[PDB]
Length: 173
Length: 107
Length: 62
Image (tube, rainbow over all chains, first blue to last red; front, side, top):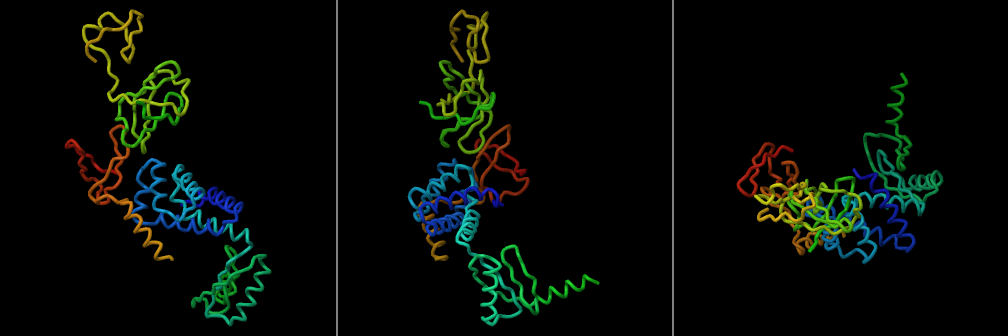
């Protein structure tokens, strides 16, 4: 797992993309790079021990959606360090850093059934106060939970469901 | 022509990298100009792509990274036969008794 | 774009003819002290006899 080795590269790519106001192009370029890693034949090539500067070039060849200097350069550096497999995570941490910079959040809402779309409005309005970020909602439906709602905002959850209340009462006794 | 480059130097162990076609075989002897003096390396391992780990047959001091290396395409080979009688030689077969060239016929 | 992206990737790989090995065949990538690392051999089975050039064999242990 590349959660830790991807942080420097995601940070550098984001700081560079900001200086040039190309954050959207950088994000799309990374999303294409992380897909080139998943192809069945390319994943074979990334494992076998090729010299970094020929692996990097054969990787650059399969991508013409990377801007001439700066995407190609990122690929060359990661290839030199042998970390091209980390791209799928560089992308995630880039999206995360972007969401932090533009002050945005995406909170999950899990319910026994769809909400009234006034409830959703009040939920978004309340969370945009709990969090300084403008919040997207993507309501989800689960029926093990049976009443109330779960609000999950990253690693913060508000267990409003009645299922939670039941499991929390049973263990009081 | 010299086709390889030093990439590490850690004590007596030297790493060299060649194009992935012309990698020296194990126990092949390399040669590099450690300043105004020649130095030969014995390939100990082929590891990874293009890179080769070697043991220096002399003082490792003075080596830079990026020095050109030439791959002698034969193991360390020494003079043999009647011409080596009465002479002192080092591991590489060179005279260290100051009486001059050996006069070998066969290595 | 999600699907056509993978289609374009497959196309462009076919263009530069990067290819996987045959399942019964692989390449040496390292040699030392009588142990070799082979890249490929998806169908090699533990304990198999692998045939090298020069009519020699290796036993696949790892």
